[PDB]
Image (spheres, rainbow, N blue to C red):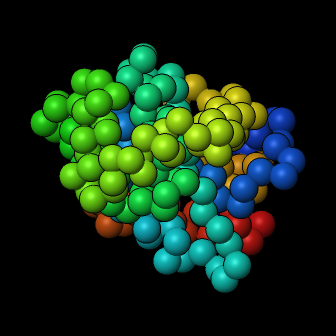
Amino acid sequence: AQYEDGKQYTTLEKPVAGAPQVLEFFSFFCPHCYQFEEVLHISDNVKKKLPEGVKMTKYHVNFMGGDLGKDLTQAWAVAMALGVEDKVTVPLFEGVQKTQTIRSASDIRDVFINAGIKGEEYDAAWNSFVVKSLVAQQEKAAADVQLRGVPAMFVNGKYQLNPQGMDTSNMDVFVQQYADTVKYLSEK
């Protein structure tokens, strides 16, 4: 076939019931994730090809960057709760991997302040039980699917994208193969 299990994707031996339609995992410490966001705009190009009625979920993971890694999962929960993902994603990536100016929870907070989220609004969210349960959701979804590596994308809790098996000579061709694969899996 043109799309082959074990080639552009793999199948989960243990399918995950009730999982989000398109589920993406990343870390702000993850170098391919930086590329996926900044250079390739994967999420964005997947969305543009997904049919109507399909929602996209993106979660942060704990297993990179130790203590700061967990702060970042909680900060991402804050970002989701306030709906400010599109304003903090780039400065968080660059703060961690480019300028290396993010070394503490306080530095993460600064990024939100500079993005215009009010200090008071941020700290209330940070400490909120709504954000607690949002952290729990990120952890549970990662736990459900055996996750030990990022970036990762899962479709309908049953298929996992396998980018190692796509041509990387050309970045644009890679992205379209990737998005077209999500679409195919989506319709599966």
How many circles with numbers are drawn on the protein? 0
In the rendered image, the vertical position of residue 67 relative to residue 101, given as above or below:
above
Judge left or right: residue 24 versus residue 139.
left
Q: Position of residue 54 (x, y in %)?
A: 68, 72
Q: Position of residue 93 (x, y in %)?
A: 28, 43
Residues 15 and 78: in front is: 78
Residue at 77% x, 66% y: name it: 188
Q: Is residue 64 visible?
A: yes
Residue furthest toward the left? 99
Q: Quadrant of the N terminus?
A: bottom right
Q: Position of residue 15 (x, y in %)?
A: 83, 42
Quadrant position of residue 51: bottom right
In the rendered image, the vertical position of residue 5 relative to residue 135, given as above or below:
below
Residue at 49% x, 57% y: name it: 82
Judge left or right: residue 145 versus residue 46.
right
Residue at 25% x, 24% y: name it: 103
Residues 6 and 45: in front is: 45
Q: Is residue 76 visible?
A: no
Residue furthest toward the bottom? 52
Residue furthest toward the front? 120
Q: Position of residue 7 (x, y in %)?
A: 60, 47
Residue furthest toward the right? 17
Residue at 13% x, 36% y: name it: 99
In the rendered image, the vertical position of residue 106 relative to residue 83, given as above or below:
above
Judge left or right: residue 186 versus residue 99.
right
Residues 46 and 107: in front is: 107
In the rendered image, the vertical position of residue 69 relative to residue 21, given as above or below:
above
Quadrant position of residue 172: bottom left
Judge left or right: residue 42 versus residue 168.
right
